View (cartoon, rainbow, N blue to C red):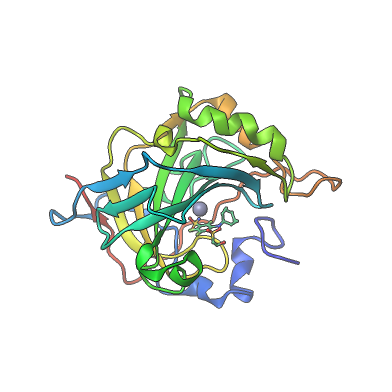
Length: 258
Ligand SMILES: NS(=O)(=O)c1c(F)c(F)c(S(=O)(=O)CCO)c(NC2CCCCCCC2)c1F
Ligand SMILES: [Zn+2]
């Protein structure tokens, strides 16, 4: 009876195994654009992905991860609100059963069709497993997806999904360039938060880009053909693998713009 996204094991149940679910800096949150404060002391985000080494893509039974070699400074995030250098380890998405839902963060209560998370860890802590135990251990760059024109840089991901349909399947995924998933503007909101999945650790500096990327209806439909179940089990479509917005509590969301 492990955690997941269903009626019986979804986000409203998580607190029973992971009490930090009702903590003081949980994610995601609603971004109220009117009350976010412009902070002119925030710096531009530095996204240095030119040397990224993708390795593999994995269906983990909740979503899929695209994994990177993080054993050297190859793909790093710095600047913005961050001190020091954060190394890209993986990215993944959350998405809906319908185009009107799927994102974890919301913007003035607006849900997007999906949300991309590029997960990076603070190199001062040496490994990811050490970084997640620290209040400034992770930086996750979140990017909203809306349905419209196709995103050409997403298509290599969509095309490999049929090879990892079920839980525990993986496939080689080299030479993928995550720059193709970025929107044009790096304007962002930022706040202190958590992993949005168990173990819900409060170790994340969230950086959420204001500008969504557009993906096509055919692209997101392919996401919705994945399966939460393993091979040779009844089909449970992998959809609605998002956690709702959590109370902001004693936090301020800062804007890098306007
Ligand atoms: N949504 S998130 O960006 O807070 C996040 C992380 F930051 C994170 F570090 C990870 S992790 O896999 O690197 C360490 C915790 O497992 C996941 N993991 C999920 C990735 C796919 C989303 C659905 C749940 C399965 C693990 C993860 F979801
Ligand atoms: Zn995520």
